[PDB]
Image (cartoon, coloured by chain):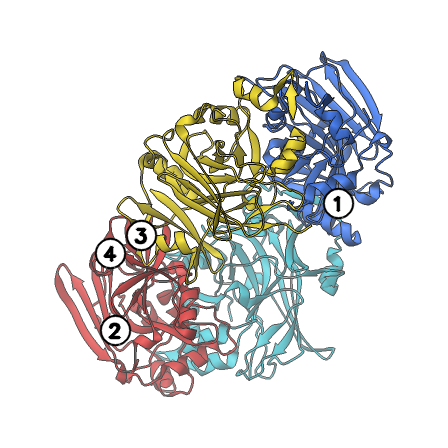
Chain colours: A blue, B yellow, C red, D cyan
Amino acid sequence: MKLFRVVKRGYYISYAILDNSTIIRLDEDPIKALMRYSENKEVLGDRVTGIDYQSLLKSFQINDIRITKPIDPPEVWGSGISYEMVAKILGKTIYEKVYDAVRPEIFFKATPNRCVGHGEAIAVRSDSEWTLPEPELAVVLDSNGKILGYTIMDDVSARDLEAENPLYLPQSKIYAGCCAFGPVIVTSDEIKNPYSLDITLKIVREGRVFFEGSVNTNKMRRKIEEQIQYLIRDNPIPDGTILTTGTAIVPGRDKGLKDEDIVEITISNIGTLITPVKKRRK
Amino acid sequence: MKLFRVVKRGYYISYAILDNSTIIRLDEDPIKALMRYSENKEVLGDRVTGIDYQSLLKSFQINDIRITKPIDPPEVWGSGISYEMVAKILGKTIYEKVYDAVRPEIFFKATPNRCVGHGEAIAVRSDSEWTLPEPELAVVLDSNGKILGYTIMDDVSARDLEAENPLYLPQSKIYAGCCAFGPVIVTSDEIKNPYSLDITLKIVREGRVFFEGSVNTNKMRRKIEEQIQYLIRDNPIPDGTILTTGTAIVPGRDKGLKDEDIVEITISNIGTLITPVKKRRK
Amino acid sequence: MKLFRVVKRGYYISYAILDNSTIIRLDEDPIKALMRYSENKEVLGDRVTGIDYQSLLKSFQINDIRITKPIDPPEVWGSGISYEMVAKILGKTIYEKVYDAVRPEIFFKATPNRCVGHGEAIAVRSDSEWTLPEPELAVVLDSNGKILGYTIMDDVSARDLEAENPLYLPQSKIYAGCCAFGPVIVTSDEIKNPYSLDITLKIVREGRVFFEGSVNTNKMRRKIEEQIQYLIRDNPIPDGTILTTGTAIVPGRDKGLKDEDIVEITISNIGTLITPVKKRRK
Amino acid sequence: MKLFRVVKRGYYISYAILDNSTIIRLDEDPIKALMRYSENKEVLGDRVTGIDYQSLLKSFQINDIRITKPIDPPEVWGSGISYEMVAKILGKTIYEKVYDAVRPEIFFKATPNRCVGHGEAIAVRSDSEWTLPEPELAVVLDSNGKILGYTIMDDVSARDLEAENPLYLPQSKIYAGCCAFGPVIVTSDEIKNPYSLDITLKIVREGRVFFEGSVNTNKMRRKIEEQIQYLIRDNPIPDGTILTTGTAIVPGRDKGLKDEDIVEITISNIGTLITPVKKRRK
């Protein structure tokens, strides 16, 4: 099952694609719907025609329906340095110490209103000279830490403020439009092996491929279930929480984002998340 | 006005004390009520007798009413190193670089369900050997960053995990019972000078004053309005957000919290916030 | 307990008077509150001062509080010809046949929005030349038919349309402002004997006692519990239904109501319900 | 447009048939949806397949969907003696006086919870020996009295209690299961001439046509818009009110309903409303 959501005259409607490319309109709340599928694979709703999923992906809007965030995630948490490869602890950089330590990095990324979806604008902080997208695999979680599905997430990071001091990390990570995900949430059975997926980042400036990069999830050192385990320890998370698993694609110092740019992120079996860039006014 | 809230048979009731020690039961939501007072000092409700504010402070519960968090803060943000006085940037420690830099530290502290109030238990992470309370002045904010009132907050911090690596800071700061505040929210006109208040920390173990410390807010280097300014920049905050302003009282390596302890925090004009300690099971 | 309700800035607040003239503000819905008292006589709320019940009765409004209907009755049912003393069945008038028959009269009187309260205007139909108030004792009922309390009701009746044909009875009885009740609902234990109460009707025109009449409930032939029994038979009634028990005070053909009139109805132990009259425009 | 509604796992879903036999699932509340069509004929929703309208009509339930009342009518009002052809006024029977008078009969029939729909059981009062169905054309109304659509209604009447005394009419007309309507609500443009429709009543006992009768609406003396006019005069009605227009098909004294019977009512362009009969236990 692949689940997406549209906004129509100020209200939401959630749809799901079954393997045979038939579209079902959901009776239930999308998060609630994912928990059900996670148990017995039952889907409650009616089969619809006239919903052009393929056009929605390309054109975002058709008539009076517009695609958006597939769900409203109550909490979004991140996890950095999970692939194989200035502030320093006794000679070693903080990043490489965490790479080797038992305890992974876990941080609070976003609230639902700080997130955007397919075809909506991510933002660059008014006071950042160097902001990069971080293309990551992300998981949707229930309150016990059970994986309800997968999606593409863009962990938008004001890399310059982070470099200045690791104590500025929250300011670098949490802001309006700091996070984008979609275009769907694929159920768990739609991905046989999560550690064998291709993630591709493209930044597009005035029709020009300004950056192109790729990495496969088989290069992920720190496994997903360990990230989950450390996230939920003594820490209650609501149903529909998203944990974003980290990035391997890191553009250079010169590849910093700016106004009008287009960030396209592709992951096998999920699709391509396209977000325009809007630079904040001081 | 001094505003508190009780839980009675599974529902909340909000009350407010006017200077002449008369208690008013509120018609409005407490956050909504604070926004009103912030404009024209109007309070909507009826005068009540039989509500023993003074007993509630000492005994927490009377008959079927129990005092709790005065409001449900949609977001709680912290701000460290704001008073005058290992990871390091070119010789200098990360903490002292932020002490001198233009940009203050701002971090996401808690969601409302991760907070507790007067007479409820703060927690120590199951995997922390050294956790300290951080006694701080805290402000209640509207969406524009206007100060709606003041309160006492305990920024409960797993100091050992933080010391190990600054990237563990979120794990050290965000968990169930990681934050406590109360016992009231005092309106802005109840504090003529916020930079002239006495904050006192006491940890009590088996009847014993295990730690006692004090500092006055006139020692606050980084001012409050600057913390607000940096918090809201490109970052939308909901009505009733609490920003906690930082601590000067830091117990030693040997004064780490444990099960059954009592943390009492006193600030002039606000009162005394008392929270028992509960140590988490692995 | 004597329970009343005010409207304050577009919202309701319910209060209750305990025998010792102390006023309690209710935590619960008034209908829900009556069901509780009906079981164990428990009242949930806080004691208030500054609510001037006695002024409210006389002046209707004080500052920003105005007295109104004590509850929103989901259904209002009437019962005619219950005291001892043209359409006709085999010589006898329909009214006198029902007087003698086993089966009492039961009719649907009003929906909640067709009702008004103490100090609000009852109406006369635009097409009625002869409308009279019918001063009656009324009972508040739970879904099983248990008496939750008593009140005063004015069954406002377009007597001329009724006289023309008994099939016009619904049109004579159901309209905007066709019904008024209050000023309180007295709990069941506040009336030792319901069949020993004085009901008094006064119509007041330009300061003038235009009509004065009285009757005692000891003259009630058809008992209340029989009316209840016939009302609920095969007929589900919601909690807080009001059944009005019938009238003995009937003004003459010349005493028909008109614009600006004042209808005052008094019953022992309950009080005096005052409603101005407004004549409808064609 | 022809609009119906199902109950599925404790919740409602509303569908509409467009002339070309395509089924649309509604985004809006059905009453709200009818008001929209009444203005500009716009319908908000998605085209569905797999909803077998024709099976629903015949079998009531398929899988986990069951057809029911097409809407929840806030108020149901009746109107008797509207076709061309003991209590008496000066020699003439009350019924024939109303037949000739300017003022039609209007009565309150039911609340929504006293109504049932296609395939659900109408009831006979436990104390009625002679109850008949009254097959009528019914209109759905907005608050101004504008006709939003048409439906079939069964005005179930305890004819014996009515005959005994016209003051028992409410008891004869208002009870649990006293009213049934459906199976759809047809929009106004689906009926070119409301005064040219065939209404057919069949009572079925153990496979046997126990009664069969028919009449055409061209025999309706008292017109519909006059009934509306008299209904709303000084009397506010909510959106989605149903007014039932009266019957011409009256079975004999021997054709009284009983347990297990099947009442089938057919009207041109609307369909056939089928309701089993359940006799009440004393």
Instruction: Say whether mark 4 and mark 2 are on the same chain.
Output: yes
Marks 4 and 1: which is nearer the front? 1
Instruction: From the viewer's perspective, tell me whether residue D208 is left or right of residue D281.
Output: right
Image location of residue A152, percent across then percent down: 75, 32
Looking at the image, residue A131 lies above or below residue D41 = above
> Does label 3 lie on the same chain as label 2?
no
Residue D194 x, y percent position in the rendering: 57, 56
List the residue tagged with mark 3: B46
Q: Quadrant of residue B139?
A: top left
> Marks 4/3: CA distance?
18 Å
Amino acid type at circle 1 is: Leu
Element assignment for label 4: loop
Is residue A7 in view? Answer: no
Letter of the chain that mark 3 sits on in the rendering: B
Q: Amino acid at mark 2?
A: Asn
User: What residue is disc 2 on?
Assistant: C269
Q: Which residue is mark 1?
A: A148
Q: Nearer the viewer, mark 4 or mark 3?
A: 3
Give the Cα distance between marks 4 and 1: 59 Å
> Distance between the Cα atoms at labels 1 and 2?
64 Å
> Residue A51 at x, y = what percent?
73, 38
